[PDB]
Length: 117
Image (cartoon, rainbow, N blue to C red; front, side):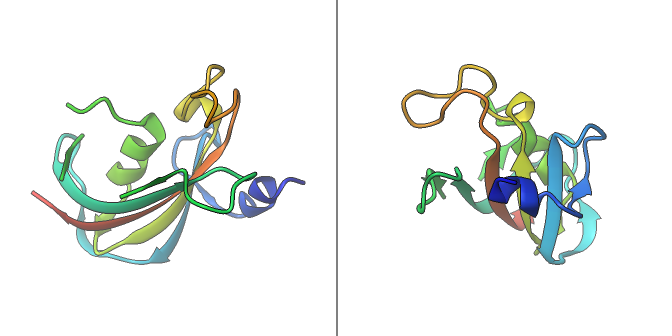
């Protein structure tokens, strides 16, 4: 009954294991992002104990990329705005990124896919 647990209610499971959950807030149009494309995005990332994004916004899907973010982008279409929840396996894991991100944190990302080429 954390809020993130509540939000995860009825979200789309793109990964199969509930590790990457998605809510489309505005649909795009046309083709889905290609497996190695270079996307143009605006993103914000959130942790639950915080009231500000922990991180706020071109991107090649060679970059050392957040796994949840990569799988998320692959599900998106141009013009789309979606919110995602990444469980620890798809985010920062057991280690986290101390002291900013604790061990075993589910993070929330809002991503807007402006374009990809």
